[PDB]
Amino acid sequence: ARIYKEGEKVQVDCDLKQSGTLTFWFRINSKGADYLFSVKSADIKENDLNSEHYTVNTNSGKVQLDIKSFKKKTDSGVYVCAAMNSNKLFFGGLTRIEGE
Amino acid sequence: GVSARIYKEGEKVQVDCDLKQSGTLTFWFRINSKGADYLFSVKSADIKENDLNSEHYTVNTNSGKVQLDIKSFKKKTDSGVYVCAAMNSNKLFFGGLTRIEGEP
Image (cartoon, rainbow over all chains, first blue to last red; front, side, top):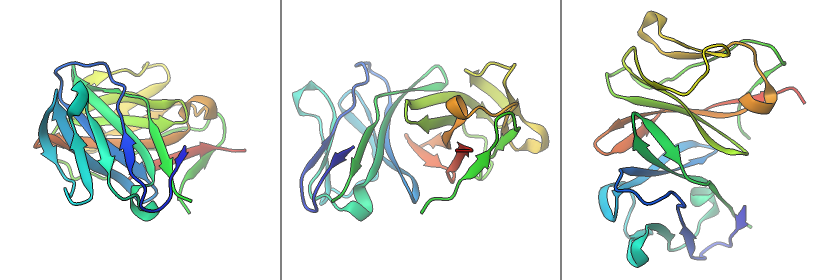
């Protein structure tokens, strides 16, 4: 459970094995499940994020979520990536991030 | 805080999904401190994939609502946050979370 101060940069990764499969990113916090974006290899398929505050970085042959300015209220929780295949989801390792 | 339901060992648990019924493929899973664990998926009333053992879990489709029925609760395996997620437009739409814990 990485702790971050207000305004710090945060990088969230996904350790899923590479495939060419549609992969969803989302997060779970105390207000609910919140959908972030989806990719297939390096191509964005849907993005609910404001570009001002969040970047989907596809440099270095992998995909990561960059939070430009951490805010406890909004960005705290469990981050999940899920690859879909065979009518099911395959999950990566969770990343948990909190404030103070 | 966070609202949750508390169960004794061996109680039945019914988990619901408040997503509006459309006929969109819907993934059911749970998150605990070991990770995210995939459960089953359903399109309307039709199972499309089920990783659950029938002896311990039943996917109940009576009423044209889908419920997961846990036959006999076990805190060590069954505690966590249960999620349902419909897929459309290359994204997920989530129902309200259901958290479930054992007695301490």
